[PDB]
Amino acid sequence: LNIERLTTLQPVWDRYDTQIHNQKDNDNEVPVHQVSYTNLAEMVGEMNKLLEPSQVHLKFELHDKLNEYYVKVIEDSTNEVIREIPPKRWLDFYAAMTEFLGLFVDEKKLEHHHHHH
Image 1 (cartoon, rainbow, N blue to C red):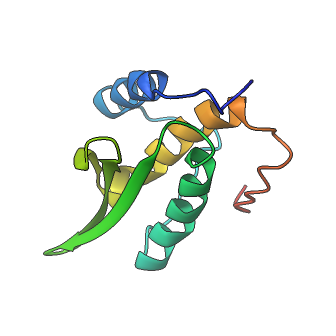
Image 2 (image 1 turned 180 degrees about the vertical axis):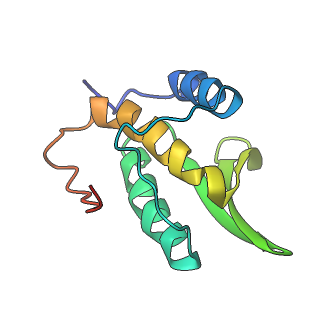
Image 3 (image 1 turned 90 degrees about the vertical axis):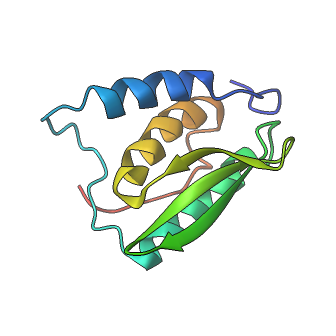
């Protein structure tokens, strides 16, 4: 597909809110990792460089609070946080949007190899 004309994350929210709200007990080779502070930057890094060549200019911010450190999604067009994802749900969001974005991007140039299978 073509991501250069992609502006929306509706299909992502569709999936994400289906998942988060209807949580299951099943393994489908879903990325399961202990989300350490280093792990945030890892997924956030590749996440940004996937959306930059599109209209979906989301600016992901890492902000720590009390015991947690979550990634808040700031929409560049409005300069406000439209979505806040805690680290313990970031893995699902990561997959949710990766399936979506990887349908647009050339599933060869992605070279984002998280070796845990």
